[PDB]
Image (cartoon, coloured by chain):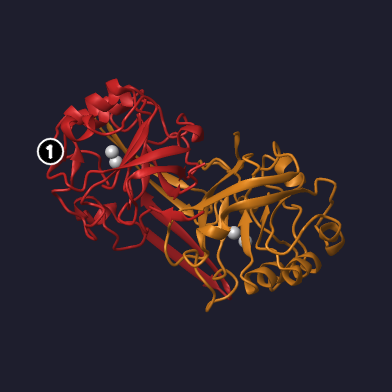
Chain colours: A red, B orange
């Protein structure tokens, strides 16, 4: 029984989207004696997080409306580290991908220590498939699940079929295969996302 | 397989320590058409959270040094909702509490939906016993594990023997007995605590 921690470290200087200074977290501390107490400011879309429909809608469901039963369940890691530029319907047709599947995608982003602007992303063609195939949720090892797609069709195509999106996974030391996924978000209410601790278990039970 | 969410909701207006209005979380939201994006600010000791040795020491370990192997593991939920004022050595001698047990304390705090200044707490006599018995960790259904104790002897007795302190649990709907605990902290580096999503499973094997 090994736990693989596939969560991104949160710290000032961490890889953030487009390396934008304002997307960086701040931690303030105070030590009155031996008592050390901190406060953290962070974008909900920081490192390992779970997107909610409200991101890409407006009467969109929040983080809260997505049940823990959908996040603390079995999952399948798909190795797409052979993929260049973007994941296409081709790369996900040939994989074991059924209805109510939670698929985590290990791509060459798992191996970038700093932000890469040309990160492998889930194209609309790939997402529209995944939606009509009837997957439960998709995780990507990238802070955003899509780029170079204005009107955000990838995102919109998942959250339309209430498919939970997990961004910011660190899947370097993970082998393609089925695992017990623990995707535990901060119990934030009414928001477009929540930062998450995502663990894999080799439970094989 | 039933998950029990024993994590407090995080929202402006939530119960915080002594109702200090500065300990309240903040959130800023932005809406370019249908993209919605948020930023949270919160005390790392807000609601359900894991304490680190740093709080109550300085050479003491930060919230990245408590491994997930001792936070995502079998737990014992002990009923002490018959206890008044404070938990004592007598109150934790009678219970099936063993070395390397992770013990979550259900008390009258779970049935308090607002902060109460007279909260049940773990007293030094009890925290010392649990320290020399060799428990792996103790969870409390109060935002703080002690009060009316200057020098913080309960904290220190436990963070001294690398015993983990988990605070802010919501154990009203939780029957005394064994569970699988997922105490999944936000992966913030070099801090005195980190907010946690704590889940309880009934897998029993
Ligand atoms: Mn995002
Ligand atoms: Mn997104
Ligand atoms: Mn605390
Ligand atoms: Mn504390």
The spot of residue A35 in percent (x, y) is 58, 70
Q: In this view, does B9 lie above or below A33?
A: above
Check the image and name the residue furthest to the bottom: B59
Left or right of residue B19, residue B33 in this image:
left
Question: Can you identify the residue that label 1 sits on?
Answer: A148
The image quadrant of residue B147 is bottom right
Residue at horizontal 52 percent and vertical 43 percent from the top: B10
- Total labels: the figure holds 1
Q: Helix, strand or loop at disc 1?
A: loop
The spot of residue A9 in percent (x, y) is 37, 59
Residue at horizontal 84 percent and vertical 51 percent from the top: B84
The spot of residue B187 in percent (x, y) is 43, 57
The spot of residue A204 in percent (x, y) is 48, 44
Decide if residue A124 is in sight here. no
> Which is nearer the eye, A99 or B165?
A99
Image quarter for ligand 2: top left
Residue at horizontal 74 percent and vertical 52 percent from the top: B119
């Amino acid at each position: 029984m090994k736990i693989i921690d596939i969560t991104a470290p949160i710290y000032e200087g961490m890889p953030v989207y487009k390396n934008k200074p304002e997307k960086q977290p701040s931690i303030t501390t105070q030590t009155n004696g031996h008592v050390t107490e901190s406060r953290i400011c962070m974008d909900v879309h920081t490192g390992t997080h779970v997107d909610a429909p409200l991101h890409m809608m407006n009467d969109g469901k929040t983080i809260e409306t997505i049940s823990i039963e959908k996040l603390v369940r079995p999952c399948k890691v798909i190795d797409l580290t052979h993929v260049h530029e973007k994941i296409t319907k081709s790369d996900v047709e040939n994989a074991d991908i059924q209805k109510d599947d939670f698929i985590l995608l290990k791509t060459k982003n798992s191996f970038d220590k700093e932000f890469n602007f040309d990160f492998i992303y889930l194209a609309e063609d790939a997402a529209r498939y995944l939606a009509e195939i009837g997957i439960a949720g998709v995780g990507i090892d990238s802070l955003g699940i899509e780029r170079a797609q204005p009107e955000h069709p990838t995102h919109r195509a998942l959250m339309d079929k209430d498919i939970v999106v997990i961004e910011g996974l660190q899947l370097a030391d993970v082998e393609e295969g089925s695992y017990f996924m623990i995707a535990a978000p901060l119990n934030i209410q009414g928001t477009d996302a929540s930062p998450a601790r995502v663990l894999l278990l080799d439970n094989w039970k």
